[PDB]
Length: 110
Length: 186
Length: 119
Length: 119
Image (cartoon, rainbow over all chains, first blue to last red):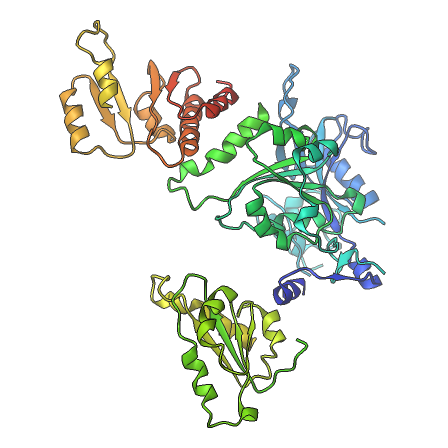
């Protein structure tokens, strides 16, 4: 419908807020969450990915689907690199480290 | 109802269709699952994007001193290698997902376009209904412009080129963007 | 949009500031042929670029009921402004025939314009 | 090439056992072919691109003493030529970071880009 409106007018048209549009506002958005100081801080220190997935989905209706992991995290020696790589859909028994970011789909809250 | 899954192989996906609680609840191994039969406008008309009243391009253009005076943090810097005679790239496709009304107004990220104003005036007629968008009419290759927009504090720098048709050799089409990247890292 | 047009002729033109003139007077003289009374004359509205139409205008400025909408034949808003659902005829013409090299692709604009109006 | 070979392969130059390998995607014409034939015992030519690592492996850039990059002094846009040469330097240093590079720069403000390459 928005495609048809934009095709007709060649522009985006404003409008007044109605309960239907405000209900249409509620969706999910892509986000990255850190495990350093969040509600999953304790679980991110050596815990499994599946427990994080289940807890997030059950409590906040949050869908975790990947790990943005610091590249030099498996090395014993310390490193100054801040680069991270993508791990898509890790298994249940995948081990977490506190310096990890979680791809998630978060609900809208007013 | 159709459902979308992420999986390594398509054989495990059929378990979502063959599942039944009667003779699969006790089964622990997933590979053992079988087919046993047991007053003011703030959004657009559809209300799915943040909207603002149209504004002239003069009110969003910043000078280098003006950009330095304002403090930008957690913003998006879009460096563009455009021209007065070059193919439009459709910058609205970059700005609509970032004004998607899933986000509150305070969660929206400021967008600063760094590039030629002769190119950007030809794009502005599709971008003037979005709230927090500004222009620095300079060059992505100049360090003074990058320091004016606080590129060390942005959430993302997006480097795009528009003069792809002009360059004949395919491998040399990326010389600007690559150089721009190597500039910012140094 | 304020003025009401009915039983008129809408001439959509795919012109340009640097394109061959097509001689629009040859379209307007037979429609102002004095066989018709003044009340029987059909209003002519040209929809297209004003850079091309200014170059045409020096041979069309002596005819009574001719107007210009400086827009695009491919935009639906311009077509709704001239009440294209009430016209007697819509004439779709192109002027950039020399620019396109491939012969079969010379008609892409006009054809698309037609398919727009029908939808 | 004629000026570079005239100075490099001078008759009064002390005996240096250094061969010259030209790498260029554009095939040489009759005059370049004759010039390469005149120095067939010291000069070889290969068709290829610096930006392609296969061609860099062909000319044995990993064991070459140096790479010399010549510029187009007669070009419409000197900045584009300088950027292309800087990208050639980036490609060579990405293949082999320790090779010595002598390059020609047209404009003075462009050579600062060379300081952005850590190699």
